[PDB]
Amino acid sequence: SIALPAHLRLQPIYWSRDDVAQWLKWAENEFSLRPIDSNTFEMNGKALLLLTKEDFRYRSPHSGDVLYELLQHILAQA
Image (cartoon, rainbow, N blue to C red; front, side):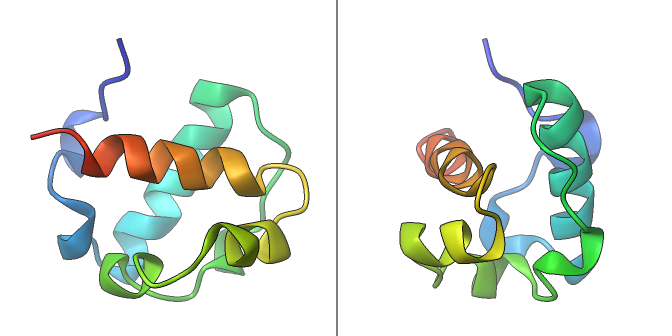
């Protein structure tokens, strides 16, 4: 199964700008994604939630849609 590390176990809506950077750092190792600059999503979880799939793909051509589905999958948790 796909379980978030203990430090990020809260609903994304509550992630701070630094939780976002920490989720990107984790996803990259966990999922073997391309290197993704940490200052790529300079925003918090609330703002992260407004972005479309197209937007994620804009910020990251390679990882883009994977980071999006991971987030959707996380939202469907609880």
